[PDB]
Image (tube, rainbow over all chains, first blue to last red; front, top):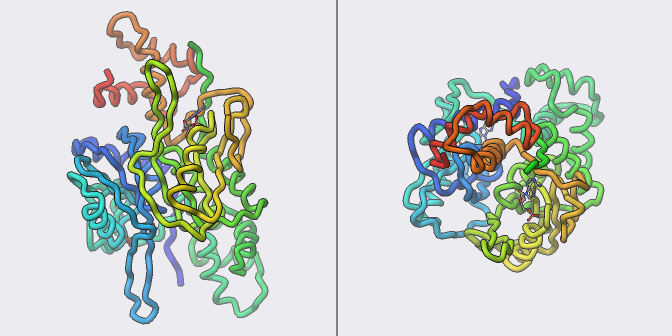
Length: 209
Length: 209
Ligand SMILES: Nc1ncnc2c1ncn2[C@@H]1O[C@H](COP(=O)(O)O)[C@@H](O)[C@H]1O
Ligand SMILES: Nc1ncnc2c1ncn2[C@@H]1O[C@H](COP(=O)(O)O)[C@@H](O)[C@H]1O
């Protein structure tokens, strides 16, 4: 019931993305086109592009589905489309490789539908114990699984982290102090980036509570 | 020869994106799909999506061309594609509306090729004196033109700001000191986010110097 959670700051993001870009520079892979995996790869993609000097960024939206009986995970491109990337070197970027299902799909999808000269993959982080596929480049290796709460994800993650606590209440009333307490107890965050009261207001607006 | 330049921080970006999202909430425009304009709108798009709770983000790459004799500006979609967005409300996002050429193209392109039920435009900033087109939503109105140096653009902008000084030199100069001095004199930046020596090394790697 405890989930190890790490709050990632903008500075750490900048540091990771820059470190990622440096590895690509040092490998002298000449990138013409970045394909960001939406939504997680949008920010890292922009930052890496700034460091490497890439002007062409495209994105594909990859969904993550779980079959509720079998619990089978499946990644899936939504709003799929084709463009002609022949004669381009492509770099695919995402935030973090966990199982590697997303980058595996992205690579396969790009090879088949964009037809680049060459394709490489890159993520800010990479979880060694969990990854079936390892990205060509990564800034930081993670040897112990944890949920990484990125600065572009603060609202969404907190909304979910709060909901995982609320769905075990046993009282259709919501006590905020109890909530804050459980947040510290379950996740180890005493000062969430977004105050839990704002989260609750937004959860109501979204009809989650 | 002096260019007014404002260095925008991550916190200001967060503040702007959140303020932008709040306007959209208050207007009760129910967004199904965000179309980010690459590259400038990628980050703001992600952040606004986090605040509003939007899961579907697509992007289109808009280029900005100038004809060198006539000086005619033209915005252009690169790697154009079509997807079916019928029955969706779309929000198009970019960093800043200057002339409004980009959002005008984006809106026209999205209406014609994605065919959404409805399309609105949004930028973090909006320059009143320059904009032919005004976005449906903006976080901050600017009444006096300035170059906004965004945190996802620090390398690129500094590379250009340095180049604009170097292309008036004297004789293949070096000296990180005169450069730094001119930077302060021309732009008013005493501490660039990226150190100028860092920029120079990267300029050589890119064969700009
Ligand atoms: N440990 C984690 N922390 C934060 N985000 C994650 C984590 N694992 C997976 N994700 C998200 O899930 C997506 C898919 O990762 P994967 O399991 O490699 O397909 C990534 O793009 C991340 O946005
Ligand atoms: N004053 C400015 N500061 C920073 N970026 C700008 C500025 N004006 C234009 N841009 C960039 O140029 C693009 C086109 O703006 P527009 O002139 O409205 O077509 C925007 O997406 C910005 O990324």
